[PDB]
Amino acid sequence: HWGYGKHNGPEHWHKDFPIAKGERQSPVDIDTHTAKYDPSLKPLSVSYDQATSLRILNNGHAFNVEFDDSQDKAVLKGGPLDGTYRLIQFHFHWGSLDGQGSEHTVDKKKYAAELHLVHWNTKYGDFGKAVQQPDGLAVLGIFLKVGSAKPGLQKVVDVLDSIKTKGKSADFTNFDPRGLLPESLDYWTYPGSLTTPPLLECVTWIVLKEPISVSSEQVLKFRKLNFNGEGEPEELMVDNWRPAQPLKNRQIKASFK
Ligand SMILES: NS(=O)(=O)c1ccc2c(c1)CCC2
Ligand SMILES: NS(=O)(=O)c1ccc2c(c1)CCC2
Ligand SMILES: [Cl-]
Ligand SMILES: [Zn+2]
Image (cartoon, protein in one colour):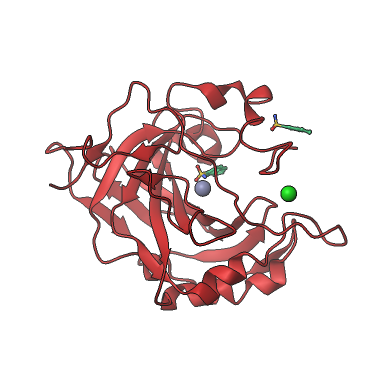
C-alpha cells in the first residue's frame, strides 16, 4: 500500500487519498518572519505526570509508543486549544542522513527528525470520533537535532531491536514522555492534518521552537529499523517524512515575540 518509496511515496498518495491536495494539509514550512505573535493564545499546559505507556509498535511506517487513554491522565490544554486533549501515542519521523528527516521545516531548514505526540479532543469520546471533527486532534511537534544525547530517549532506543520489523510490538510500560521535552514551550501553531494517509484534516498543530538534542548513536539506531516484515528483504526505515505542503489560506501564529 502507501509508503515512502519511489512508487508509493508522498507524490502518489493523492490517488487513494484525494484530500492529499486539500486546503489544510501538513506538514508546512514555518516562515518565522511571516508568523505573527498571537495575544489571544492562552498559556500552554502539558501535564504528563500520570502518563501510562503500555506498548511500542513498529507499524511499518514508524514506531508508536502507545499510552492508556481510558482515563484523563496525560493531557494537553491551553495555547490555541479549547478543552482537554488526551495523549494516545507518540512517534517520530526521521531521515537517512542528519541533514533531513523532519516534516515541518523552519525557514526551509530541515531537522534530523521530528517527534509527534498525538492527542485527541476528549469532547468527542474517543480517537475514532475525534478524527471526524475539524478540531478532533492536537499534535505536539518537537524537532530533533544531532548533538548531545537525550537521556530520556535511551529507553526507547534500546527497545527498538525487539521491534525491528513491521507488525512487531513489545511491552513498554512506565515510560515518562516528559523526558523528551525541551526547556522552553515557545511554539508556532496552525490548523492542519495528519501527515500520513488518511491525511485527515482534523489537527491543531503545536510545533515547539526549541529542538531537543539527540546523539548520532541514538538516531543511527532509529535507522536500523525496517519498513518490511520479518523474513522479507530488508528495507531500512529511513526518510519516513512527508515534505512541506502548500500553506494556502492559513496563518501560522507564534506564542511569543
Ligand atoms: N496512492 S497510494 O496510497 O500512494 C498507493 C497505494 C498502493 C500502491 C501504490 C500507491 C503503488 C503501488 C501500489
Ligand atoms: N504524523 S501524524 O500527523 O502525527 C499522524 C498520522 C497518522 C495517524 C496519527 C498521527 C494517529 C493515528 C494515525
Ligand atoms: Cl526504497
Ligand atoms: Zn507523525
